[PDB]
Length: 165
Image (cartoon, rainbow, N blue to C red):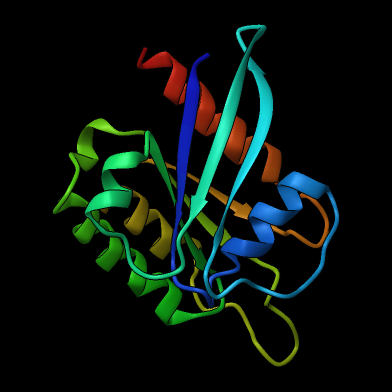
């Protein structure tokens, strides 16, 4: 019956695909998806059973997508200046087609890609600034490799969605 529609939004160097796939499997394959996909998952909020629909487009967001969603997860990777900047753009461009101030948002920075060669580049001070430019939305870090916060993100969003019904 009720239908939680969540949109994942970020460029494809952001690790957003690993994070969706971690959620649905609980395991980690590397490969991203240059054209996204649609997904599903029963979850319980208030001991009632909702169906979670997950559109990850790939490209920017458009009218058709922006109208469909009920909430939007914005993703960058903590080791790419451009995944970061592109969130500020895609936000602006969601505002073109929806009222982003009346819509559950979650900002997510991903760790997976950090390492010896690729050192982290977005310190906490800066993510905190992005969180505020997005109306001080909730924020998270995630490793898809081992688990961190992947559940919390998606249960966080769903709670917000039901709570507006």
